[PDB]
Image (tube, rainbow, N blue to C red):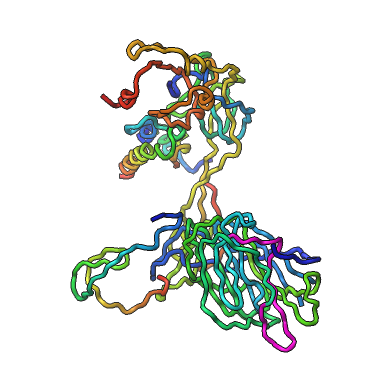
């Protein structure tokens, strides 16, 4: 396993709302001059997400383990390249197929193995006194990788990272969704220019590359980088700088937006179909111009809460010893009818003696027996052979 | 075996539940599961029946197999929602009308 | 009063209550019984509006 | 109290559903 | 030949034919069979669509 830090000042984060962000292309079909609806995972407008911080020239560096849900909207405002890669898995202990997509300064290591992570994985760089670049020295991601299922190596590229401080310069948004075997990644770059806060602009995210793999993602964790200059000792005690960045963590919800396609085919406007009474009218009428009148929408329904059961109290068990697994029964033409009533009947206790080999219920579901009440349960006991079981069916001659 | 043709006497190994009246919860009388408010009843009932259907062939009254009382069935799904707006070119104020 | 009699009809099924078929038949096998009830009511609503 | 006459009031003397979906 | 949870992405082998336009004949591009005249257009689509 990797190492950890010492004395982490975790400040209570704040909460921010969305500003028309989290809209992408649900399908790969070109559509223009058409207004309709699409049922897909998106981020609802004017929601409430957790706003994390990482400003440090204190000791603001927090990266908890958040559970992964169906559709996670991640928007990081990197002005000096602090947030590197991300991890996806369940227990993170070399016991399941985990996803490791780290944005290394040399290449993009995308491997699906069984890595071993510590308590707080991160990246470590060094600031040389003679070289003004930002090269990577420490590598505290994993420890070993034996069984693997996928490996991807990017092309060699030269990237000396960024040192810009003050205001934000680049915006990197990533959407991670787990749909069966397709892992869609929507990456979109937008050169923003502001101090802080989420921009109020509207843009459509484009997919990068789909990974047809079969992994089980339950929890994720955002990995960052630490700066170690010559003024700091460079140890894992107090000689480390968190940096200066901020990322937004949001979860997608099954909503429905009103996509607007112009002559170029890009998404320029999105109106929610279930949030405000005014925005719902635009989606229902399939038009952005609402006239002055009266309209009819949904009705009024109340969902129930508890569920009471009113069954008669019966403290008697039906004799399953003489009916099932006995000594002898009757013939096929002289079968005897036994009345079974005034007792509690159940089919789950019929496996302790004489395991059944053919249990096919006709006219009733085998799992819906205990749901409905039984009344006048007659048993037809007869001993036959195996060549006559196929003929016993309601509708055979 | 039959399904909904005679008073209960067997059923399954399911336990009981405390009666919660004046609520729009899910009830279950003699296997029949429905949804409605178990209000009071002031009408007459023959001392040898169980269920009770009206003109619309709906479950009206039903005798409890434990407390032995008549309780009516009335679903709480009664209402309508309608929004009236003067238009998006005048003001962004709406008025939710409850029918 | 005509629409009330349509809710009590089975349209060639086993009952007329949507809470009774699901309580005795599993969803993967009761899909052939619910479709007969919906189709039988669409013709009644189309005739009523007509 | 109404805005009718004796002849108009005489015409008016000669002349559960919402639980299923029949609203007036 | 095994099939995992991910959909199949390798459909081999795969042949190809010729190309003809200005005729109301039958064609099959991508995975969609159509019938019409392959007339040139003026607008472009998206690189991932």
Q: Nearer the viewer, residue A61 or A289?
A: A61
Quadrant position of residue B44: top right
Q: How many marks?
A: 0
Q: Position of residue A21 (x, y in %)?
A: 56, 68
Residue range corresponding to the magenta coloring:
A114-136
Q: Position of residue A203 (x, y in %)?
A: 52, 73
Q: Residue at x 39, y 67 (%)?
A: A29
Q: Residue at x 79, y 72 (%)?
A: A58
Q: Position of residue A237 (x, y in %)?
A: 80, 69
Q: Let me know if residue A280 appears in the view.
A: no
Residue positioned most to the front: A146
Q: Residue at x 79, y 66 (%)?
A: A6
Q: Let me know if residue A362 appears in the view.
A: yes
- Examine the rendered structure and indicate whether residue B19 appears above or below residue B80: above
Q: Position of residue A360 (x, y in %)?
A: 40, 29
- Examine the rendered structure and indicate whether residue A258 appears above or below residue A133: above
Quadrant position of residue E30: bottom left
Q: Nearer the viewer, residue A244 or C35?
A: A244
Q: Quadrant of the C terminus of chain A?
A: top left
């Amino acid at each position: 396993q990797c190492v950890n830090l010492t004395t982490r000042t975790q400040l209570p984060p704040a909460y921010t709302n969305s500003f028309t962000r989290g809209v992408y292309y649900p399908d790969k079909v070109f559509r223009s001059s058409v207004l309709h609806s699409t049922q897909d995972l998106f981020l609802p407008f004017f929601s409430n997400v957790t706003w994390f911080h990482a400003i440090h020239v204190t000791k603001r560096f927090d990266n908890p383990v958040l559970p992964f849900n169906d559709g996670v909207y991640f928007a990081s405002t990197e002005k000096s390249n602090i947030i590197r890669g991300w991890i996806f898995g369940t227990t993170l202990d070399s016991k399941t197929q985990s996803l490791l997509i780290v944005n290394n300064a040399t290449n993009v290591v995308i491997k699906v193995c069984e890595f071993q992570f510590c308590n707080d994985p991160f990246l470590g760089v060094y600031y040389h006194k003679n070289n003004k670049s930002w090269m990577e020295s420490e590598f505290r991601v994993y420890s070993s990788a034996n069984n693997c299922t996928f490996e991807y190596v990017s092309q060699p590229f030269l990237m000396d990272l960024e040192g810009k401080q003050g205001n934000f310069k680049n915006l990197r948004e990533f959407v991670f969704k787990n749909i069966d075997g397709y892992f869609k990644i929507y990456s979109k770059h937008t050169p923003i220019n502001l101090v802080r806060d989420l921009p109020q602009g509207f843009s459509a995210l484009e997919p990068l590359v789909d990974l047809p793999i079969g992994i089980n993602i339950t929890r994720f964790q955002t990995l960052l980088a630490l700066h170690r200059s010559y003024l700091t000792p460079g140890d894992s005690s107090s000689g480390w700088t968190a940096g200066a960045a901020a990322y937004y963590v949001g979860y997608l919800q099954p909503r429905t937006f009103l996509l607007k396609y112009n002559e170029n085919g890009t998404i320029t406007d999105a109106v929610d179909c279930a949030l405000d009474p005014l925005s719902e009218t635009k989606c229902t009428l399939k038009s952005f111009t609402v006239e002055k009148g009266i309209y009819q929408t949904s009705n009024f329904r109340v969902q129930p809460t508890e569920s009471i059961v009113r069954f008669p109290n019966i403290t008697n068990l039906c004799p399953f010893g003489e009916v099932f697994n006995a000594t002898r029964f009757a013939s096929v033409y002289a079968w005897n009818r036994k009345r079974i009533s005034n007792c509690v009947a159940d089919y789950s206790v019929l496996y302790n003696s004489a395991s059944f080999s053919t249990f096919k219920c006709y006219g009733v579901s085998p799992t819906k027996l205990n749901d409905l009440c039984f009344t006048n349960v007659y048993a037809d006991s007869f001993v036959i052979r195996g060549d006559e079981v196929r003929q016993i069916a309601p509708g055979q001659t | 075996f039959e399904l909904l043709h005679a008073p209960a006497t067997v059923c399954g190994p399911k336990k009981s539940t405390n009666l919660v009246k004046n609520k729009c919860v899910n009830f279950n009388f003699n296997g029949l599961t429905g949804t409605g408010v178990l209000t009071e009843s002031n009408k007459k009932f023959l001392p040898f029946q169980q269920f009770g259907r009206d003109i619309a062939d709906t479950t009206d009254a039903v005798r409890d197999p434990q407390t032995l009382e008549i309780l009516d069935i009335t679903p709480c799904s009664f209402g309508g929602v309608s929004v009236i707006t003067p238009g998006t070119n005048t003001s962004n104020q709406v008025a939710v009308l409850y029918q | 009063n005509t629409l009330v009699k349509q809710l009590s009809s089975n349209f060639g099924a086993i009952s007329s209550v949507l809470n009774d078929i699901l309580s005795r038949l599993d969803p993967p096998e009761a899909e052939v019984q619910i479709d007969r009830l919906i189709t039988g009511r669409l013709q009644s609503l189309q005739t009523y509006v007509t | 109290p109404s805005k009718r006459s004796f002849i108009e009031d005489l015409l008016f003397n000669k002349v559960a559903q919402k639980f299923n979906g029949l609203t007036v």
